[PDB]
Image (spheres, coloured by chain):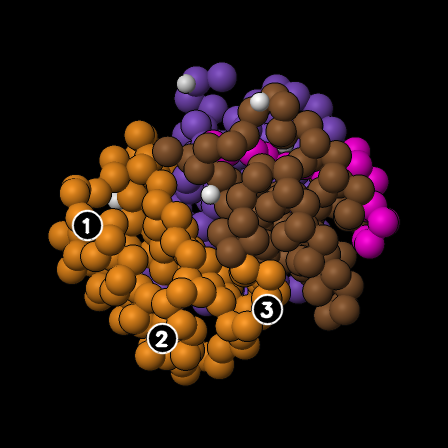
Chain colours: A brown, B purple, C orange
Amino acid sequence: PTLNLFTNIPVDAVTCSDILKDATKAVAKIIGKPESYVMILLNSGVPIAFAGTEEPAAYGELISIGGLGPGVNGKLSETISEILQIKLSIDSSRFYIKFYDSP
Amino acid sequence: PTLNLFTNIPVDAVTCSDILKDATKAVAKIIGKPESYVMILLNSGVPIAFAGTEEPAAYGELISIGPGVNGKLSETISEILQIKLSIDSSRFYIKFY
Amino acid sequence: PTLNLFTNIPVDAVTCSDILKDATKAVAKIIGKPESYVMILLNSGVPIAFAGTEEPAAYGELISIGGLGPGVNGKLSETISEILQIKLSIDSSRFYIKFYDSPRPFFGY
Ligand SMILES: [Ca+2]
Ligand SMILES: [Ca+2]
Ligand SMILES: [Ca+2]
Ligand SMILES: [Ca+2]
Ligand SMILES: [Ca+2]
Ligand SMILES: [Ca+2]
């Protein structure tokens, strides 16, 4: 699976590594795939307008070949959102994650 | 909806904010929803080759998007980028639909 | 088609232009469409973890209108991975590509 994140916060290198590590663990654990199949990207310092403001925000695309659904997506969303809340102070109302179950 | 934009033009902060605001207004009007439903990202200074040159170019992905809206929407964003950045070439893709 | 690349190493403008040009020629030849239809993007300096590590890596999304014939995806994957190997020393084991078969055309201007 891949998680491709974009945020308007300029993230420092240490915080970036922390997020990549935390997201790797969360994606592997919750979908049920080995970490060797999990890729996380963090595009930071990307200007974002959401709801008419440029307050801190993030966008993510989570793509998996199977393994998604109502019993998984809610947990992934909550877990990744909490990582960005703690590490970047991004409110969950300004983080949109799009899930896609790929053929 | 989310519009994820990429351009090889390096864009200054004010022009970026103007584009984000212009695009927010245009998307909101064309889709008929409040701005609280609209996210615009601008990835700038991303090298792009299009039709075998690196002339000014933009690429946009539309996520979580009425019929015909996509064409009027993509053309309007294309016009905004031409006016604000002098980008003469652009491509828009409806993603995950 | 569009190839949107992301890599975690910094890439200088000359190397970037080489990658963009070689990727344009390779995608155009393998897919059979003229270069006028090919767009390549290179997002560099993007932190990536793959298999739990941050060694040089790349992600690519290849978006084609209607998808490609049997075997063509694998040929594209191999060819792009060689470009990234030659130009950036990214091992092919750390290149991850996703193909999108778009059921509707791009909007181009
Ligand atoms: Ca997968
Ligand atoms: Ca389920
Ligand atoms: Ca949205
Ligand atoms: Ca329609
Ligand atoms: Ca095309
Ligand atoms: Ca195509």
**Does mark 2 fall on the same chain as mark 3?**
yes
Sequence-first disc among 3 and 1: 3
| CB atoms of marks 3 and 2 within 8 Å | no
Q: CA distance from mark 3 to mark 2?
A: 16 Å
Rendered location of residue A78, percent (x, y): 75, 34
Task: Give left or right: position of A16 versus C83.
Answer: right
**Does mark 1 fall on the same chain as mark 3?**
yes
Q: Which residue is mark 3?
A: C54
Q: Residue at x 54, y 49 (%)?
A: A34
Q: Is residue B5 above or below residue C104?
A: below
For numbered disc 2, what is the local secondary structure? Answer: helix
Q: Residue at x 42, y 21 (%)?
A: B68
Type of the residue with mark 1: Val
Q: Which residue is mark 2?
A: C85
The segment highlighted magenta reads: A85-101
| CB atoms of marks 2 and 1 within 8 Å | no
Task: Give left or right: position of B79 versus A80.
Answer: left
For numbered disc 3, what is the local secondary structure? Answer: loop
Sequence-first disc among 3 and 2: 3
Q: For mark 2, name the chain.
A: C
Sequence-first disc among 2 and 1: 1
* Image quarter in which the C terminus of chain B is found: top left
Q: Which mark is residue C72?
A: 1
**Does mark 1 fall on the same chain as mark 2?**
yes
